[PDB]
Length: 147
Image (cartoon, helix red, strand yellow):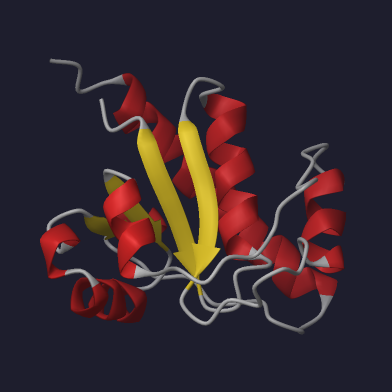
């Protein structure tokens, strides 16, 4: 059971906390946390990410952005992201975790997901919908594959 996960995106404030909370919604006992490759360390969750989460009654409350570092990569047992470009950076940062970085859309023909950054709420909702199905597939795998 890879109970300890760190989700990662570029600016941190959006996809990482959305994924964190979606994973917690489907597995309350999961230790899941959120960071970024070029994080806005100290900022809260993005107002637009909060808005689309609240439109599905999920609460990105109390998120704090965190620059991922080699120490953070060692701290968890599965590193999770949304794009294969980010897998490449994370493998370069922590070769010791290269076999343990994967993406949300892995279970969907390894499809990668846009980053909503500052685009309209429709973009935030489109990535939220992608993240929601991906989080269900990750939760299904987490629930299964017991040993």
